[PDB]
Image 1 (spheres, each protein chain N blue to C red):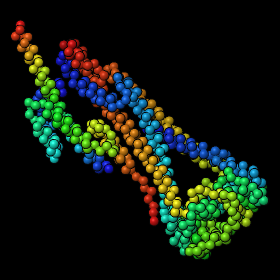
Image 2 (image 1 turned 90 degrees about the horizontal axis):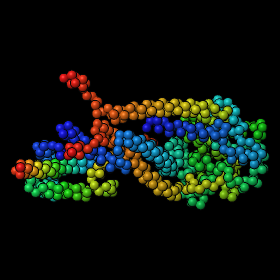
Image 3 (image 1 turned 180 degrees about the horizontal axis):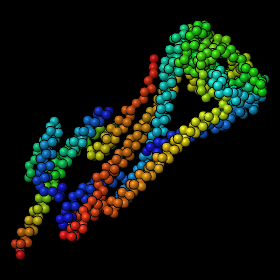
Image 4 (image 1 turned 135 degrees about the vertical axis):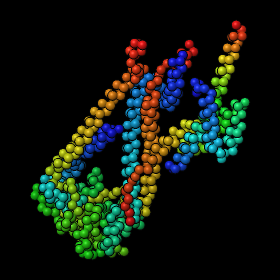
Length: 98
Length: 247
Length: 197
Length: 50
């Protein structure tokens, strides 16, 4: 992004915020943090919002089947699980009984 | 400077994707040829992991088939035998011996030999008309005559020996059966053995799960590298523009 | 992936053919040793040459007893019986002349594609006609050749797939080299016009 | 299982993307603003001193 003008950066930021408002509608902690983040004169608030998001995700990982703490890395493991489960779903068809 | 500036963002995007990709792997890439050789090593790991996966699959299939033979109703060649048991006024022999203890089970299994899973039918002439119709049955069907409710020991020319039994089946014919372990009859503890088999098959299921997961991981890694080269080589491994612009 | 698949199937066929150890189709040597230990001969060895047309009928007739020793005495076995431990778990023995083996005692009655045998008092045995009978083997070379035909078909398919993969890899190397040495100028316009200007 | 994992993956993949973009774009905009401020300071300093 270093080789872009500020107008494009603001456009992306605004559209991302538009998506976030809907994504985070139900939660309250994240909603409070996002609310606090939008004053341009206090930048660290945005990174604090980011930290809140990451922690919130880490609680929901369900490590019974997954081990990565970083969610971004956890995406690949969910993808692998989908592929493997779809493969197991194939067929057996040895059906014969009383 | 204008040329370098136009070129820079593409090179930077390419570098970020490359760093993510190689860091995701254990080995660090440095050139196009290097990436290709890494492709080849990835293929070799695919085709090894798949072989172990398939072999474990074969073992698991054998285990389920073995377990299934011991299931129902009195574990036998159940596919046709149950219908064949009711289509004549008879009872399955293995079912008559459902209750026998573990100590007499090997003896009886040796005694009855292949005929363990025959049917008891007290006349054997009433089947003679039905018989021509039997086109759907095990390749060797055994029939015995006696009272199904209080069946007497079939007249065998039997003779007990050390850990074995001798029998005269016919004039000029004898059979000699050695005591097996974990027999057919006594289908009370044969549930004990299928319990042992369930415990055995659990491990195969677990191991197969891990192997399949590994194969999928390798396949997706190859997909990632292919996607990369599809979208990336135009500027891969080129010299850093930040430096030259600074200069 | 496909050439590896075909190689695996060809291994399976080769394993199946190898399982035809001796002479063509494996026969248990331990039974030969037992036939040596008692005066007699292995039954399949007696009927190994019967016609393929009647072979399924005979195999249906004998059932499990197909693998057994023809001992005309039955006096040598009984003393040695308690000495037998390595033998197959269900050993079968028949009495008759090994050189000219008279029909075994079966009250056999022939049904449509099946046989019925009154084995004993209060016992009948019923069997259907199989294929690949133990008798009338004649080495069953035709089955060995059918398996060889299948194996050679798999080998040919494997050869074609290996050749195809080699072609594809060569094309890949060509492209790698090209983007390594001409990509910087690929698809650009002719400089002579600009030089003229 | 496929249903549950599908839902989890969709949620993660969308929320993480929006959070990351929203935060990082602003971070870079601040970096560029600082660079502009430094350039302005140096230019006006240079011509003032000269």
